[PDB]
Image 1 (cartoon, each protein chain N blue to C red):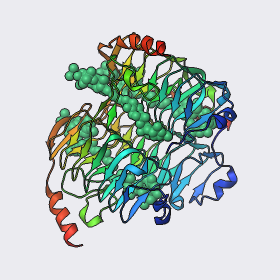
Image 2 (cartoon, protein in one colour):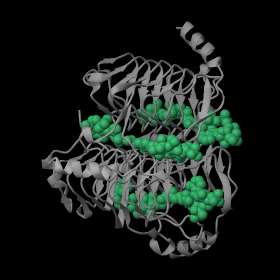
Image 3 (cartoon, each protein chain N blue to C red):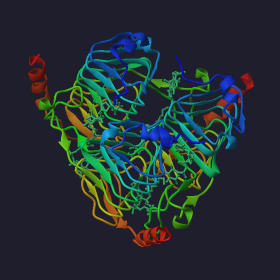
Image 4 (cartoon, rainbow over the protein chains, first blue to last red):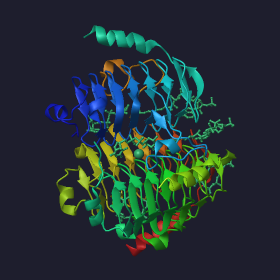
Length: 186
Length: 186
Length: 186
Ligand SMILES: CC(C)(COP(=O)(O)OP(=O)(O)OC[C@H]1O[C@@H](n2cnc3c(N)ncnc32)[C@H](O)[C@@H]1OP(=O)(O)O)[C@@H](O)C(=O)NCCC(=O)NCCS
Ligand SMILES: CC(C)(COP(=O)(O)OP(=O)(O)OC[C@H]1O[C@@H](n2cnc3c(N)ncnc32)[C@H](O)[C@@H]1OP(=O)(O)O)[C@@H](O)C(=O)NCCC(=O)NCCS
Ligand SMILES: CC(C)(COP(=O)(O)OP(=O)(O)OC[C@H]1O[C@@H](n2cnc3c(N)ncnc32)[C@H](O)[C@@H]1OP(=O)(O)O)[C@@H](O)C(=O)NCCC(=O)NCCS
Ligand SMILES: Cc1cn([C@H]2C[C@H](O)[C@@H](COP(=O)(O)OP(=O)(O)O[C@H]3O[C@H](C)[C@@H](N)[C@H](O)[C@H]3O)O2)c(=O)[nH]c1=O
Ligand SMILES: Cc1cn([C@H]2C[C@H](O)[C@@H](COP(=O)(O)OP(=O)(O)O[C@H]3O[C@H](C)[C@@H](N)[C@H](O)[C@H]3O)O2)c(=O)[nH]c1=O
Ligand SMILES: Cc1cn([C@H]2C[C@H](O)[C@@H](COP(=O)(O)OP(=O)(O)O[C@H]3O[C@H](C)[C@@H](N)[C@H](O)[C@H]3O)O2)c(=O)[nH]c1=O
Ligand SMILES: [Cl-]
């Protein structure tokens, strides 16, 4: 079976914008669909949470349990980006340092929230159980491994692993040739 | 949108005690609520689980996916403690050594469950995707980083990271001041 | 207060096979029950996902949030095997190298999915927040620590930790007697 909303159910959600062949679990949470644009051929799985400003392009899988906290600044994924299960992407984060109170029970003037657009460029893949922090551009074709923590921007076409991640090898570009192949045959 | 119970449904859950301005997700799970006590200005998000003895004070966020397995001995959080997404706090665990059978499918006399009260003191923040094992006090003002694992009590006012955690630098104490300033404020 | 199906609703799911004393959360997701079999005395908790080909023996707990993506080649667990919360087992994963396109939105010609049966032998325990990848045999009596990642088969009766896992000590085998002793009671 599957848990995906109908085309009929989907247009009732109220997305800023939703494309063709979009498959979204009835078990995801979508908060403020008003600020969420989704392109074509996108699958969002069980127990995802998308909240605040989120832009997804086309050909992207958001695997189960993944939370995207877009806040005001937003999270944007370009085409052919994918995110494996249990990832968190934060576009805002509280100050852990001891210099500020923390979290949504507390008025902003006591906190020191860090906020910044998070961008995943084309062909980015994020491995399972990973965390991406605010104000981070994940460069084109970057792979980050499972269980990775990314606190700053990542250079294009590299593979990274660890907490926090380190650059371990080049990502191959064959994928770009297959993109063009795939598209050409449509 | 939002997924919270109204103050009216909350009253029907049958909590040991629940204060005001409590926002609990309808997508969270609550088992044995008659041993669960929640103070004022608490938020518990989608997909959290609270099970068995759990005591939360005030000005606390339990972010999404976080499981608090309080068992019979309990987990207690003091005021201004917050737990980030996908954290687990166990007050009991099975013996992994090979010296016992394991899990809820096996009866106790063949197991060797390790149990003990867990306490998160005031101003503790627990980073996302972290695990706290039983019989542990997380010190006053401690921050535990993301993806960290805690098996022992932690000294006050430090930041710890890793699996298992190590101390990396003092937590700043400004928040004590901010706590007074904020509380004055009302 | 628990969230399990009755034995009656269980039969309405359409498992290849379901034993007795099987406690499955209504909050778990089960996809393609037709290829899933479960033996006796098994508990599957909230927000679990079982997808594709999955075979569970007896006396096994699959804890909250755990995802078993059995695909076509399958995941098998033998008796007395248990998986702690927020674990992922994959029988298939995409190629992260950059030599292929990725994920369920892309046709198979353009991908290079690696596939392989995952087997957990008797008495295996997998710690919370762990990830097991395809084509892996976890030998009998293996314990994998929390927050660990397994890409290769594991030697029987050892304890392994880390990302990727390294062997750290033997598992005790007192478990083997206890099993005999307990089964006698039955
Ligand atoms: C990143 C990954 C692609 C690396 O695979 P690889 O290219 O086969 O690299 P190796 O296995 O040789 O590892 C290279 C180095 O990185 C380390 N490493 C590999 N993956 C790591 C990870 N996730 N975290 C930390 N270290 C990692 C290895 O220990 C090795 O270190 P060394 O050079 O110090 O020995 C793979 O390990 C991974 O993390 N895959 C994620 C799969 C996934 O999440 N899939 C979702 C379902 S599609
Ligand atoms: C713990 C944290 C606050 C430390 O950040 P920082 O004070 O800026 O410290 P740095 O990034 O300089 O790192 C200091 C050391 O700890 C390591 N480190 C930092 N965070 C780590 C983590 N979570 N796990 C393991 N190692 C970590 C760094 O590698 C560095 O090691 P080194 O001195 O051996 O090089 C931050 O890394 C973190 O984990 N934040 C969690 C945020 C979160 O979960 N938010 C939830 C939503 S509000
Ligand atoms: C694997 C585990 C059982 C080991 O515990 P232990 O036998 O008491 O071993 P120790 O705590 O002495 O650690 C031994 C070594 O392994 C390292 N280690 C222990 N657990 C680790 C883990 N989960 N990840 C990485 N390293 C780990 C230690 O740092 C130590 O390293 P060193 O030899 O380099 O100093 C335990 O740490 C663990 O992970 N338990 C998982 C519990 C769980 O998930 N329970 C689910 C609820 S029932
Ligand atoms: C996870 C999930 C599955 N399903 C249904 C519909 C699907 O067609 C079917 C199988 O989905 P699946 O996710 O088990 O299998 P796949 O479609 O192969 O995808 C999975 O394996 C890949 C190698 C990974 N890259 C993905 O991250 C992982 O989700 O089950 C749902 O309806 N909702 C879900 O959340
Ligand atoms: C996650 C979640 C959200 N919501 C709704 C109600 C909320 O007011 C709204 C916004 O929630 P949000 O969590 O997206 O955004 P914030 O309210 O800023 O909270 C979040 O960012 C912080 C900087 C972190 N420290 C928190 O751990 C993180 O959860 O969405 C729910 O109703 N239920 C939920 O579980
Ligand atoms: C997690 C969960 C709990 N429950 C209900 C019925 C249960 O009998 C009761 C308590 O179960 P619990 O998981 O809170 O507690 P326990 O039955 O002790 O089990 C737990 O502690 C062990 C030491 C760990 N090995 C397990 O991984 C952990 O799940 O709550 C549910 O109905 N559904 C659930 O998903
Ligand atoms: Cl999760």
